[PDB]
Amino acid sequence: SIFRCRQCGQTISRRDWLLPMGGDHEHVVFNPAGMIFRVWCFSLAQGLRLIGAPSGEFSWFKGYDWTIALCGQCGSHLGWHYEGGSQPQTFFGLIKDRLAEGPA
Ligand SMILES: O=C1C[C@H](NC(=O)c2c(Cl)cc(Cl)cc2Cl)C(=O)N1
Ligand SMILES: [Zn+2]
Image (cartoon, rainbow, N blue to C red; front, side, top):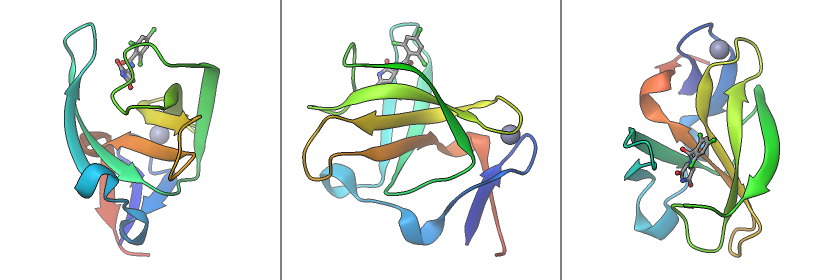
């Protein structure tokens, strides 16, 4: 029902807020360092700290620029916030295995 940061327990998001971007909330992707991420898309999230300036470089989602999303509490890299696109303008792509699911 809710998703917390796996490292410290910070409240991050909810199952109800999963978003099927391109028909699926799950997207498996790699960055230029070859790191594989299983990214779940969410319409909304909280408890994050978004860092740096948005960048389109290597964006996995056409038309969106990303900013890195850290856990606001412990600093763990939890994913990205996506903006500058259309339908929707913004969303979060969070790394599934950095989250823990549990009761509200
Ligand atoms: O949509 C995205 C987000 C994802 N970005 C990254 O992994 C990334 C890059 Cl490329 C550079 C730095 Cl300095 C830090 C990070 Cl976290 C990517 O490659 N495509
Ligand atoms: Zn945390």
